[PDB]
Amino acid sequence: DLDLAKASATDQLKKAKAEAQVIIEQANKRRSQILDEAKAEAEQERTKIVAQ
Amino acid sequence: AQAEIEAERKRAREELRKQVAILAVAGAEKIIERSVDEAANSDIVDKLVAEL
């Protein structure tokens, strides 16, 4: 029974590590998206104000 | 962008100073040569030989 208990606990921990890593990668991709949206909006505003 | 426009403001001002000054002295050369007078020329000489 100890074999089963050890294996289940350790693979549960492995699942947690993988899930945390992909959670953080989703955060990183969202970071890129929002930052590029801000950059595009700012550049659009700046170009139109300087022409005006 | 806003500080950029306030730099551009000074850039616009200086060029107009340059234009008006150059064209004004261009007119002044004509005006002064046409307005030469022998007594004034003698007074220029009488000034410089008085300080020399």
Image (cartoon, coloured by chain):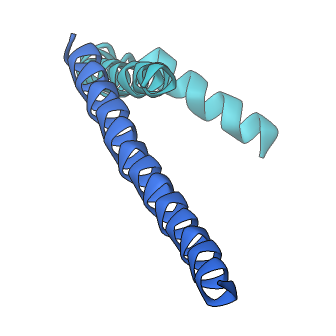
Left or right: A11 in relation to A25 = right
Provide residue A13's location: percent of width, then percent of height: 61, 70
Viewer-closest of A48 and A16: A16
Percent across and percent down for residue A50 are 27, 20
Instruction: Identify the colour of chain A in the image.
Output: blue
Check the image and report above or below for B32 versus B48. above
Q: Quadrant of the C terminus of chain A?
A: top left
Q: Is residue B23 above or below residue A15?
A: above
- Locate residue B8 relative to residue A16 in the image: left or right: left
When asked about the image quadrant of residue A22, the answer is: bottom left
- Residue B50, by quadrant, is top right
Q: Is residue A26 above or below residue A5?
A: above
Furthest residue in direction top, as rendered: A52
In the image, farthest residue toward the bottom: A3
Q: Is residue B21 visible?
A: yes
Q: Is residue B50 left or right of residue A34?
A: right
Of the chain colours in the picture, the one used for chain B is cyan
Using the image as rendered, state which of residue B34 and residue A13 is in the foreground.
Answer: A13
Residue A14's x, y, as percent?
55, 74
